[PDB]
Structure formats: structure tokens, C-alpha cells
Image (tube, coloured by chain):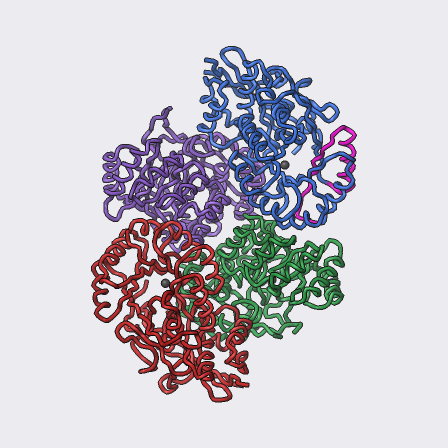
Chain colours: A blue, B purple, C green, D red
Amino acid sequence: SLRITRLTVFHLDLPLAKPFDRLDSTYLRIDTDEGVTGWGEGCPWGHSYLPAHGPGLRAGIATLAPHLLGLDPRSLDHVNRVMDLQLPGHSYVKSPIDMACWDILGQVAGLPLWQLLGGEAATPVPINSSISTGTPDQMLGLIAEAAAQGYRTHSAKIGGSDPAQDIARIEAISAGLPDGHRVTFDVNRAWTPAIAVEVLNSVRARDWIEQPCQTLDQCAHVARRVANPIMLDECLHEFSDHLAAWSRGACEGVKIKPNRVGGLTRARQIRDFGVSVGWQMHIEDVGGTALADTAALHLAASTPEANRLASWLGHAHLADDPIPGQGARNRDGLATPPSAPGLGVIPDPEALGRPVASYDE
Amino acid sequence: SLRITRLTVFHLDLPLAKPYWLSLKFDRLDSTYLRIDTDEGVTGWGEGCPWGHSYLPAHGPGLRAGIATLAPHLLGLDPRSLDHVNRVMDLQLPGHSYVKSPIDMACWDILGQVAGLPLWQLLGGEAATPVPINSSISTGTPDQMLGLIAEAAAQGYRTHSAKIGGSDPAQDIARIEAISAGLPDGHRVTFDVNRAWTPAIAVEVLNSVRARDWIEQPCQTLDQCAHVARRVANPIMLDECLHEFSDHLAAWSRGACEGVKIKPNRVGGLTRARQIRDFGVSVGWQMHIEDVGGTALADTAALHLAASTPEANRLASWLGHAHLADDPIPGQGARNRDGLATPPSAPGLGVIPDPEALGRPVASYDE
Amino acid sequence: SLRITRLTVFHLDLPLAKPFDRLDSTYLRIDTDEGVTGWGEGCPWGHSYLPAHGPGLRAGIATLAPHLLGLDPRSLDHVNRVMDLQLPGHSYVKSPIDMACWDILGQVAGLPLWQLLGGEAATPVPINSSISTGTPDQMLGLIAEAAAQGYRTHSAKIGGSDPAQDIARIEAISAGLPDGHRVTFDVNRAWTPAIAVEVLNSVRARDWIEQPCQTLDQCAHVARRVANPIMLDECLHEFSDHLAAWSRGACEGVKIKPNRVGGLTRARQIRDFGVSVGWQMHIEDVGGTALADTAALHLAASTPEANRLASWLGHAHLADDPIPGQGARNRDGLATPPSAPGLGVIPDPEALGRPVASYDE
Amino acid sequence: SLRITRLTVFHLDLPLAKPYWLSLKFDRLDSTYLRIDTDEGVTGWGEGCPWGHSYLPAHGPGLRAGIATLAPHLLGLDPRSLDHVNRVMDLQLPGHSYVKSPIDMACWDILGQVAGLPLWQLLGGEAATPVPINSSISTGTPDQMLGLIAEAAAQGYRTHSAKIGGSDPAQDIARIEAISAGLPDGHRVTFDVNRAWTPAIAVEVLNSVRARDWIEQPCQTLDQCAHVARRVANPIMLDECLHEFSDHLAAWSRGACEGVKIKPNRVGGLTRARQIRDFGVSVGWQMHIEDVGGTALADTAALHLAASTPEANRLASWLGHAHLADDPIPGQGARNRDGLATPPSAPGLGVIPDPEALGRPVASYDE
Ligand SMILES: [Mg+2]
Ligand SMILES: [Mg+2]
Ligand SMILES: [Mg+2]
Ligand SMILES: [Mg+2]
């Protein structure tokens, strides 16, 4: 008999700290007849990073609202089935909805998400830096910085059509890393296979390379020809892409991002599959405020230590904060998810602005 | 030199001829017409009309949101450079093929008018080939569907798409054997299952039946359909699981099918549909080329691609406007004349909607 | 109603600048009833390089002429279908015909080929040198030269039955290349797999190796055993060979040459396929005058920058020029295709000689 | 020591017995006879006769152009060293197998005469084995083809090649079941489709029919035929897609077929045909060995290879000269005597054309 009673949609205009200069984030409030309210966030990283954009996100909540009204939000797999029937794909639309129902379930259950996701403890999860693309000594300065801030894993954005510079970047960074630190070379689909093969086979570094090419097939091809661990990310849209990645032997790890795979319920199924096949995983969201970071972090904290790599906190990159003082935050390069029932963050609607849409029955 | 100058968006509420009931009255289609103007006064039109919002990853409100996201980026582009415009849309909004298809269709219109050639010719066709049209035969008993087909046949249809599916093998079996046995001579049927089978039910029914007609998309995924294909004897047609060119390449390398349907709104437009068409010809696929839904505008776009396809590879097209109660573009576009439809031969697309017939625009974008 | 009205065949005797000492080129003029004339060129690189030769080329135009007369040249796929029905294979015969119809279509459309082939602009395409086979310091002198001329990519012809010399060649050239320049080792089918494996696994260079062996199967075998990017060329005769190359995971790039694949319509289908699977490509013709170079260059200029490598200009190697002042030419290591409608080159028949054959209806 | 001294080219205009009409009257064959002389007065002859110019990558004018290109390079060669001559032709003009086949055939003639042995013996055969010949049964109704076969049978044919194909499954089905059911006892048929099916139509027809006779080349490519083969129950014979030895190796490794036809003009001559023949024996293929077209000269060359093939692997040969209206070499070569033909036992090829019967030479090449 618990029923979803109202969905309210907020649009947050979030300038980035280091300027696209802004993010378009959607906050979603879900009410129930018994007065338990859940919240979710979907904030695509602009509209060019993934099949996702803020105005489409809000349009998708509109298409789904009338099918979500009156569902029992405690039945998470059922909620997801209904979302899949009513609007295929659009994982970016589905994530904040699924996030908010999880929040409800955790509040009704009296348990934080990390415990519903199976974890023994609110594990402090190591956080990782983003090193933006530049020259060999530039990136190396940005790393010295991040290390001073307490990051011990760093994700260097590299890529291009120019084999020589990526070679230079990789060999400088891989050698001039502080002792005990970890670096991932994030190419974000910017190589063709020819470049990946030339670059990686010219370099002694055997660090992680993340998503070197645009497709799974192109990544698998690179993997058979080079010696580095390959991490997949943006080409994984649904569970079947992960199964294909596994069956092609394409990778040794994946990133799992709720807004890319359709929320916590889908992410958890992927996470369990990754543990079963020995993958190591970065579990984080695509972008947004500490609300999105918190949901991801509950899933990251509940992952076996052998399989869990550092998480990125998207809110580190924002000029503003709509939910100051809430969520997993960086404390000496570690973020601990909250232990209160549900998500553990409650946005104040006054901080958010006036709702851009609202659906009742 | 030529430059996109304005994009105008129209939302058309299209009633269906035959509502059907759902477990919801599915009543009407939400169609988007897009008008692209340029600085030299050549204007192109395109349509994107998802079959409601549950058929594919596509819905009307999402389509109009996508155009909003892309508009700032299309303003200023030379619409004659089609591949380039496609790359921009791909850089600026990955996926969302249902968003991209009307934009690409309008650029093709513009290109055709600048070239003074009909789309079927730019697509390589020797002539405005009349293309056979198929019937839609709704699910029911063996005796019903067979009566719905005699009826179809009296209207000039020689190819028929029989909608079967559901989790009771026994009546799917009865339907297939009945329909396949009692077709008029020279007629053809395809059994459209529409992802309704699990692989277990597919294997049980197809291996229970003597009929060797096409089975279209028995299961939800490519991987499931390829599994069924290795275990049954019928020609397999893929459709809904094919979202982009790499899925076609994957279908081909697994030997999953002997044909595909190509629908611009599913694959992102004519430029992308054409590359797939040509791939199909290279590997010997037979293909239905048609759109997902909409008025005779989306249907004419698809029919240009269908008419330019070599006869060996070309099967019947479905005309979505045949299922509509209204017509916003009366007397324009390829229409069914006794089981065949012929694309226009005017430069470009060959249809020009009257803004007066469309309602007030819901969005406009200019530089 | 536009109809092909006459085909005229010219035979050009072209001495090479650096001496087989000559090329046999065929120029083809196609007239229509509405007075729009298109031109094409097929010029095999002698008769030993590919399944192609000048006298066969002219013989094939003879077999096809009566099937081409009266076709609508604007319908390019239809023209190609008719050529395939009437004379299977013989891509070398078909290329100049298809080239001339494209020229017509571009003139009727009022658009240059690079825009009909989808490009945003007449992109200046980087040109690459040909370094003929010799000793390590010889080839290195020839490269210093080409670099002075403005070439920044160089194609070194290597190959033989002698592993030690190719090792010497490769390691000298790969190390003594000017900064920022690119080198491809063009073996032109001159290795068996045993030699390819010994050579490439003895060398630190990870430059492109082009067509190391006689067949696709032999190249794929080498590719699985070595660390360099493999570029395919001469074994690709038709689209199905490219599909097989892709499915075998044999290569990371291909060269596309109109006279080898049957013209611009076939080349474009290959080019689009290469972009879709992440290949990088050299798009150029097999040999001939700036007319053949120009057609290829329209297709090269319209290829996404991520996928496009340098083009070779065959006319650089000729003593003569029948079309002086026309076509894409080298200007500081870059060639820009023309922007006039169609091909953008108009041969003067007076410069060509007396037609060796002519077909009317 | 022995040296090629002159090459002489003849062009023979061969009328067919049965013109057939095209959508063009296909009237006559363009055949090339080549004479190779040497310094010791041993002369060899070869023939290359494509089945018109649309059947394979081959045509008469191209063949005479190819000989022109190769002549300077063959002049001076020792024609006894066959592999070597093949390598030279391969270095000097890649591909163009239709060009190389008559040159290689003439060298084999020369080699046989120098050795004082018939080709069938140099090819390893124990004796001049009479080889069964098959009929050609033209496309028509079930009742026609079956009447064309009783007729064939009365002429001594026990193997019949029934030409089917076209994009209407229903009558291909009727033809196959009719013909396969009503063969004389002891007789055999092959259904020659000649690349006319797409894979969808192949799968529909073959999986609709009880007949398990050979199907020859259902589809255009090896990859399409191998796809069909995995899904149907009939023995598959490959032919036209096999251009060179690597395609045979590819056919073998995909399990695409249980037999092949070997035609010298398609694969480049006897030297290349022989290597493929032997490969077929090693892997247990059954094979038809015959030429593409031409006079009893090309037919005798192929029949030497056919007679030397072990009986387990050897099926019927087609004799191209049976379809000609003329005969430039009357009373020479292997001819059909009541369903069998026997290659000659004279040294070399065993046929010697009279230049007087051939017209004036169209080209001559000497050192
Ligand atoms: Mg990434
Ligand atoms: Mg379907
Ligand atoms: Mg090469
Ligand atoms: Mg055959």
C-alpha cells in the first residue's frame, strides 16, 4: 500500500569552478502517501559526453511521471521494469528516479544504502583526482597539487591524433608520480586503434588505460595487441554491454556510473557481476552535486576492497553547493558515506529554486 | 556559403484510425515536423514520429528537447555537407537517433533542391520505382487473421505482416500454420513477433511448424535472436535491436539474420540509413525500408531509400500514414495506389507542408 | 532524361622522372545530351603492381561502352551496378568511368566532389613522400630531402628475403627522422610471415607497417605476433575483403585507391566503413596525373581528421604534365582540392593527343 | 635450352546452337586460340573462351590485351618449366586468370610432346578413363524440365545439371521437388542456382524441400554460401566464387561445401587447376572438372585433368563444345560418345588446330 504520490522536478544551474562552463542538473523529489520522501539527482556532464542531456532528462520524467504515480517504491526491480517498458533506453532519465526510491526504501527499512547494498561498514573510500590535459610538466604540476590535497590516485586526461605527445605525457607522468600513488590514463574515446597500439607499445608504463577508443569492438582489438590493464567506461550502457565486454575478454575493470546505467538497481547488478568475474571498478557518478556522489558512494563503500578502486567526486568541480554540509565529502583523500537511513541527504527546496515541474494524481 | 538560418518545430497530434487498448487507450501519435531555413531561401522539412514512447528509445517530448539542445549547434552549418552535419549532431548529442532523423531528412531535402534532383536519385536509384506496400494483420485466431488477409488482398496488398507473439506456444503455432498454408497464390507473409518471445518459446514454436516464412525479431536482443537462428530453419529478419551501424556489423558477423528493416527514426536519418542499406546489398540481405510512424512526410523519405534499393534486396515497405485518421499534408507524398507507392520526382524530398495546416510552432531557433 | 552520349578514350604515355621507366594512363571523356562532360583517369602503376594494365583498361571500356551509352550518369549506384553486371572485377576499368560520372553529377549539382562526399571544407590534406629502397644512410638522405620539400610523412619502401637489412633500414630511419614527422614502412608484399615476425620483433620502432605480406591471411597472422599498427593496401580488392580484414582483426588502417576498388562510389563506401570501425586511412590513387590525384583528394579532404592520414600525389613522379595548372598540387606539404562544381579539372584534348577510341549511339 | 620463340593469337567467333534472349541476343562466344612455337619446332596450343563477358571476370578483348602485355615476358622462357612460367605470368600481370589459362595450357602441350606422354598421364592418371558427361537442363516449369530430362536420358546422359534460380521461392521449390522425385533410376541431378539466390531465399527453399541433391553455388559469395550451408541439409557445390587457391582454402576452413567445380579459365590453367584438384582429393571433395566455354580444345584440356582424378572424387564433366554451332577442330579432341568422353592418348594435349580453319591471326609476337 505505500504509493508514490508526487514527483517534483528542480533544475539546478551549476557553474563549474574551472571553466562549457556550466552543468545542468536535475533534482527529483518523490513523495509517498505515508509522508516518506526520497530524492535523486541526474546531472549529465554537459550534453556531449554521453547520450544524456538536462532538457531530455526533464522531458523523460514528464513521459514517465503518469506511470510512476501510485507505484510502490519499495519494489525496486518492479519500478525499473515499469520504467523500461514505458521509456526504453534513456538511462539518464531513469537514474534519479531509481535513486529516490532507494532513498525511500532505506528510510522505510531504517538502514543506509551501503548496508542494503550489502556492505559491512561505511567504508572510507579513496578519492581520485582529475588531471586535465596539457604538457608533460603542466600535468605533473597538477598532480603535485592533487597529491598535496591528499589524492593518491589520479586520472590523467590524455588523447589526440598525435602519438608523440601522448607518449611524452604518459612517460613523464608514469615516472614522476609520488611514491605509493596510482595513475590512470583516461583517454575518453579520443584514440583510434592505430594510435592506441603505437602509443602503448612504445612506452614502458603499465598503468591502467581507460576507454582508449569509441567502441567496445575497438577497445577489445587494442587490448589483444598491448600490455596494459584496460578499463571500460563510456561504451557500457546496459548490462548486455558488460556481458559482451566480459565475453570478448576486452577489459580487466569497468567504471560504473548510475546516470549512465540507469540508477542504483542496475549499477548493483553490474557491480555484483564485476565481483564475480574479478573486475576492479571505479564506482562514481557522471557529474553533479554531492547528492549524486553520495548515491554512488554507498555502492562504492559496499564493494569488496579487492575490487574497489578510487571514486571521483563530481562536486569538487563545482563553484556552488545547493546541499552544503551533506553527503560524502573529501577528508584527507577519503570519503565516508552517511550511516543514516536511506541516502542520508535531504535537500532544502528553498536552496534549490522554484520547481520547474510537478506531477500529482 | 549556404547557411542554416532558422529551425522551426511543430508538434502534431495525430489520431490513429484504430485505437487499441493496453494493460491506456493508445490513441494518437506525437509527431514532430521540423522546418530548416537557409540564407538563400531554400527550406527543407523533416519529420520524426516515434510509435508512441514504448516502442523504441524515443518519445515526442524528448525529441523536441533534443532539437533544443542541438539548435545552437546547427545554426550556421552548411546543410549541403550531410556527413558533416551528422558528425556535429553526433559530437553535440550522442545517441538520440530519433532526434537526429528529422534534422538529417530536412538537410537532404535542401541538398536535393540545390542539386535539382529527387532523393531517390541522390540515393543512386535509376528511376522512381513503384515500391510494393505490405498489410498489417492484427493478432487474433487462425480464422480471423486469415479473413483479415482475404480483405487485405482485395485492397491490393501482396505482402502481409502477421503480428503474432505472446507466451502461449500452442496458438502461435496454430496461427503460423494456418496463415502460412492459406495464402493467396503469389502472396507473401512475414511473422512479426516483435520481441515477444523468449528463446525457449521461439525454439519450441519454430521447430514445431513446417512453415518457412520470415520470422521478424523473435526476441528482445541480438544475442537471443542469434541463438534462436542457429537452432531453427526459418529466415530471420532483424529490426528493433538494430540501433546503429555497429549492431548491423555485429548481426552480420554472428550470422544472426538474412535481412533487416531499416527505419530512419531508429538509426538517425537518411545518411545513416543509406550506409546500412548499402552494407545490406554488399552482404546480400533483403530489407524492408520504411519509417517508424508518422505522416506521408516520414513515409516519403523512407520510400526514396526504398525505391533506390536494387530489386533483389528490396522487400515491401509499410506506410505509416495508412494508420492515421488525419492528414496534415493532403495530396502530397508517396501514397498507396493498389499495393504500390511511388516516390515523387521533384527536387529534394518532394513534399512541402503548409505551416497553416500545422498549428502554431512550439519552438523557433534563429541567429 | 540526362543520358550519356559519347565516351572518348585517350592514351597518355607518361615517362617517370626517376626511371619500367613509363606509365600507361587512360583518360576518359564522357559526354551527355545536355552538353555536360565529365572526365576520368585510370593509370595503373605499370602492369605488375596490381591486377591492372593499360591495354586491358582500354579493352574493358570497349566491352562496357555499349552498356554505358544512354545511362543517366547522375544515378551513380545504378551506373556501378550495370558495370558490375556487364564486366565482373576489373576495378581498374571501372574507376575512370565512375570518376567521370561523379564529375558530371558535381557539375549538374553545382557542387565540388568533396562536398557531395560530405566534407565541410576543401581541407588542405598533408602529402606524403615516397622513399625508394636503398641503404640506411641513403634512405635517410632521401628523407632529409623530402623534409626540405615540406613532406612531414614519409613512406619508406623496404622489403626482401634478408632480415638483417630491413632491421638496419628500420632502426636507422625510425630514429633519425626529423622531429614531428611520421614514417610508414611500406613493404609492398615483399615479406613472408617468417621475415615479418623476425624483423618486427627485433626492432623497437612501432611505426606503421604497410602490407607486409602477399595475402590478407598472411598479414593477419603477422599482426597477431607483432606490436606495430598494420596498414593494408594491395590485397583489398572489394568491399568484402575490407569486411574480412575487419572481422579477422587484421589491421588498424587501410589505403583506399579508386583504381584498385573501382572508383569513387566504391571508395566512399569503404571510407565510411573505415570511419565507423575506427580505421585511419591514406586516400590516394594508384598512379597517374593530377586528374586521378584530384579525385582521390576530394575523398581524402572530406574524411574526418581523426581518420585521415597523408595522401600521396602520383603526379610528383612524372616527367610530364598534360593538365598543367589544374588539380590538387603540393604547396608546402599540403594539397587543397578545388572548389568548383564537379572534379574541378578540365583536360584540353589538344594536350592529350588523338583519341585512340570513341563510342557514340 | 628450349625457348619460346613466337606467340600467335587467333580470335574465333563461335556461334551458339541455342541463342537465348536477355533483359541483347546472346549469340556467340568470343574464343581465343593461342599458338606457342619454340626454337626446336615444338608447338603447343591453348584456348581461352569466357562464357560471354558477364559470367566471370573475363572477356575476349581483355584476354587478347592480356596476352599482349605478357608476350614480351614469355618470349625466351623454357615452356617445360611450368611452375616457373606461372610465376612469371604472376609477376608480370597479377590476377587475370582468364588470360593465363591458354598460355599455361599451351606450355603443358609442349611439355607433354617433349616427354612423349598424354596430359592425363603427366597429371598422374593410370589410364585414359572415359569420363561421364552431364546434361544442361534449361529453366522452365516442373513439367518442361522433366521432359527435357527424358530427352537428355535418351541421348545417354546420366547426370543432369538443372538450372534453377530467381527470386520466387515457390516455383524453385516446385522445380526441385518435381525433378528430384522423377529421375530415371540410377540418374543424378545437380541444381545449379548460379548465384541467383539471396541467403533468405536459399534458406526458405532448401528448408522447404525433401530433396537432398547437390545445390551448386546458391549465392553470390563464399561467405553467403557458408551461411546457407550451416542452416540447410543439402550437399553444397561451389564454383564461381572460387578464383584462386586461397578461396579454396577459405572454403575448406569454413566448412562451406562438400565439393567444387574446377575450371581452368577461372583459376588460371592446368597447373593451378591441378593443385586445387589435389587439394580436393586430400580433403575428400567431389569435383566437376570442365572448362568455362569453348571448343573441344579447352574441353580436352579439362578432360585430361578430369580423367586423371580418382573415381571417388570425380563427378561428371560438362563439354562446352556441345553448345556450339560450329566446329573449328572437326574430328579432334574428346567428344561425347553416349554419355562418356575419353581424352586422347597422343603426347601432349592431343589436339592440333589447322591455322587454315581459324582465320588470319589477330596478333603475333616474336624475338
Ligand atoms: Mg572515462
Ligand atoms: Mg519488428
Ligand atoms: Mg602499399
Ligand atoms: Mg555454377
Image position, residue D91 (x, y; %)? 55, 71
Q: Residue furthest front?
A: D126
- Whether residue D122 sits left or right of residue D180 in the image: it is right
In this view of the protein, can residue A13 be seen by the observer?
no
Asked if residue A352 is positioned above or below residue C326 in the image, the reply reads above
- Expressed as whole percent of the image width and height from the top left, the position of residue A67 reads 45, 22
Q: Residue at x 47, y 89 (%)?
A: D41
Quick one: quadrant of the C terminus of chain B?
A: top right
What segment carries the magenta color? A134-163
- The part of the image, by quadrant, that contains residue B322 is top left
- Residue D88 is situated, as x and y percent measured from the top left of the image, at 54, 74
Asked whether, in this view, residue B35 is left or right of residue A197, the answer is left
Task: Find ligand 3 in the image and state its quadrant.
Answer: bottom right
Quadrant location of residue A145? top right
Q: Nearer the viewer, residue C289 or C274?
A: C274
Identity of the residue furthest to the top in this view: A34
Q: Nearer the viewer, residue D333 or A254?
A: D333
C54 relative to A283, above or below: below
Give the total of numbered labels. Answer: 0
In the rendered view, would you say C51 is above or below D228? below
Q: Position of residue A261 (x, y in %)?
A: 55, 31
Q: Nearer the viewer, residue D247 or B329?
A: D247
Is residue C55 visible in this depiction of the protein? Answer: yes
Tell me if residue A151 is in the magenta stretch. yes
- Residue C232, quarter of the rendered image: bottom right
Q: Is residue C230 magenta?
A: no
Residue in the picture at 45% in, 38% down: B221
| Residue lying furthest bottom | D40
